[PDB]
Length: 104
Image (cartoon, rainbow, N blue to C red):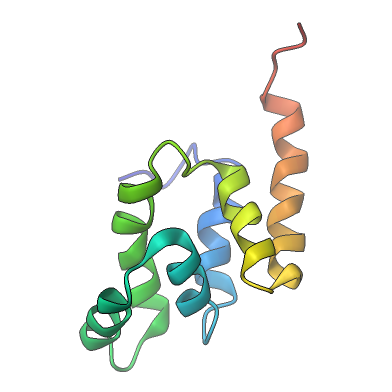
């Protein structure tokens, strides 16, 4: 696990968990979660979206591993018709310009 060092990603993982309530079913689907999963994920947490969402993470990235970068997170928000969150996770992208280095 890792509770320290996920800079920027904090907004991407905190996002999936922050706008929960009805945001994971959109991020899960767009993150590449088969419908069969929404039925399993919900089946696992019938009273806690905040918990089921974190569960996708183990799968969410397990599929788009290479395409599971920070940009994928906000980039995904844009497709989830949730520009609101995508807006805050986009702030994540701004933090990358400081660590992404690579000036040439």
